[PDB]
Image (tube, rainbow over all chains, first blue to last red; front, side, top):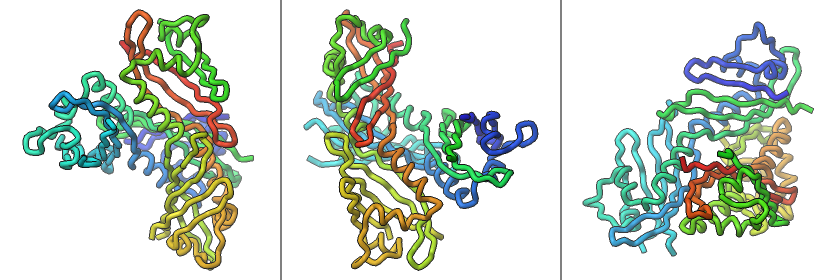
Length: 106
Length: 108
Length: 108
Length: 106
C-alpha cells in the first residue's frame, strides 16, 4: 500500500514502513536503509533529477506573499504587499530573505 | 510616487537594507531609521504584527511539502514508477532535521 | 471546546457546508445561519475582509509557478536535460487560458 | 540561452523563442510548434511523468493558508487559521474549495 518513511538528515539514517520494502522489493529484516542505499534503488536515468528536485525544494527559494498595513509617521495607514524570497546556505539555514514591497493603498 | 521598493534582511547581521523607494512607502528617513527587523515591526499596524510573524515563520520554517516522481528498480529486476510525498521538518535554526512522507507505487 | 472545524464551499451552488464544529467557533446556529460565502464575510472582521478576498483570489486564481525537469531528444539524435519554469494564467472562471515560461538546457 | 515560450490551451498552439528552437534542435522557419509536437521531442522515458506533473500542478490541489479574525455575535473577536484546498474539475474551473478552520485565539 502506501509506505511511510522518515529520513534523518544529520546521519542519513532512514526508516521504512514494511509498505516501503514491498514497494522497493527489499527485505525488512535485513536491508539496512540509508539515503545512499535508497539512491541505488533509484533508476539510474532518474537518480540525478531526483537529487536536483529534492535540493530545489529543500534548499532553494520557496517564494511567498504577505499583506499587511503600515503606519506612516503622520498616522497615515497603508496597505502593502510584500513578496518574500528565501536564501539558504548549504546547511539549510536562512542566510537572508529578500524581496519587494508594494504600496496597495490605491 | 516612488514606485516598487526592494529590501534585504540579513539573518546573521540582522541588518535590513532598504532602497530609498521603501523608505518612501514607509514615510521614513534613510539617514535616521534603525534598519532592523524590530524597527520594521514597530512600523507595522499593531493589529497585524502577530499574524505576519506567524505567516513568515510558517513559510520560512514550516513544513513545505512536495511531490517527486521517479522509477526505482527492484532487486528482482522489475521497474517501478513511484510517487513520493515529502514533508520537511526544520530546527528553529532552519537546518532540516528530518524529511518524511509517503511513497506510492503507481506502476500500472 | 468543540475543536477543529471543517467546511466545503460549493462554487456552482454557492452553498457553504459547515460542521457543527465551525458554527461553534463562529458562535452561530446551524439552523439559522445562511450558509453562504457572503454570510461568512459578514462574520469576518471588517479590517480583514479585503485582504482575505485578495489572498484567496491570489491562490485560487493567481499564477502559481513551478518547475519541471525532463530530457528531450534533438532531431540530431542528441539527448538534453531541460529545466522548465511554468506559469499559469487563468480566466476569471478558473479555466487556464495560457501557460508560459522558460526552458534551460542544463546538459553538461 | 534561456528560451521563452507560451502555450495557448484551447488550441494547443505553441509559441517559441528562437532560444527554444536552439535547445530542442528544431528549425524556426519551418517547425510548427504545438503541444502534441512538443511531446514528441520529450524523451520517451519522460513523456508520461511530465504529463502527470503538469496536471498535478495545474489541475490538482494547491493548498494554502489564510489567517483572519472573526466577530462572534457577542462582540468576541477570534483569530482563526483557515487551511484551504482547491478542487478543480477537468476544465480547470473550481468545483469547490474545502478545508479546516482552527480557532487560534488561545
